Image (cartoon, rainbow, N blue to C red):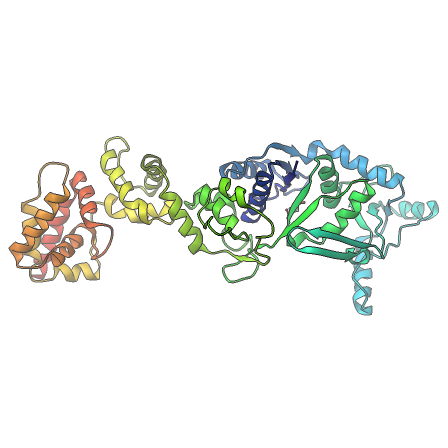
Length: 484
Ligand SMILES: N[C@@H](CCC(=O)O)C(=O)O
């Protein structure tokens, strides 16, 4: 049974990168009929707080990225890391390093000057009780380093990358596995230690990771061996790239799942999208798929082996498709607080029939749910200001005649049929001596303040239910007349 896991640190909100990894995990586990484990790497850090854990779970659930196990919290497991490290010290596979950061910096500078590989020189591997005690009496307290063999050939068959090969000397020397603490105490366990201890304990069969952390892989492989475990398979995916081709920056633009959600993007659209960022679907599947369908066909072979540029136009293309999948009643419900938030005056209960009609109208051409604000303005703001084209349209010689006909022949009854509407345009045109196009264009100007926009008959139907076509036609007629 395949076992995979998401291991986010709640140091910030759920970002697209992490969620993308979660998608690949959920997709791979589901494909292989395995388990998806969620592990929260909650650290003593200033950054780690319960509001980011909250945001992580919320976003995963919302994206439909259901875990089968957890969340298992790192902070409950502290002693397991302590045990693992103590086992390493006892075995002499780890040791106390008393080398200060100022000492490391001088080493590193002396390395650059000499054209030597940048690394810790393993200077404290074999310290004498006397040497340790000298450091301690000067008030030093040691970190704990895990021994890495310089000449060790580390290799793995990566599920995305292929054979990946590292020398032991390429890992930067004996790595710190625990932060400073006095001898007899063990400090805060570092990432590479924690992840192997937990991956071994959680029985993880396959680790899915961003390629930006590929260098931890040979380090972790050595920890598994030292702890007597066989490492799992690794799959290193390329990161999501910019709109142009550099790193997607957390400090530049929108990356968090909660922000995309806030913007009017739907969960299934986000899911479908993140998948498309790196995974190209097989012939016959297409670009519009659920997670359940993506699971039937998911494989690491088909992962685009370089960065997927993030494209707003494609996210929008998908979101439009999901918005259209929304039931008219659910869809309207999504819109109401949006319109409410804009300060638009209406009553959910009283104004329902045309509100619904407005939803029906606006649905087919929204890229985000937020687009219903500006696209609804003409139906919620009473007065219309005429644009440069509307003003020139009403300035046409027969505009007054058209409008006055329309105004005089509007039905009192609340529902305007498409039949009654076409009758009116046809008859207003006949009165003015003009073609239907110019008539509609004059009606458009009157009702919207523009010469182009949403389906006119439907816009008029909506505005008629409000009783708003009547004062608008009157305002346009008065406008036509001021030119005359
Ligand atoms: N947070 C990193 C490393 C955690 C891990 O999967 O071990 C990533 O997923 O790219």
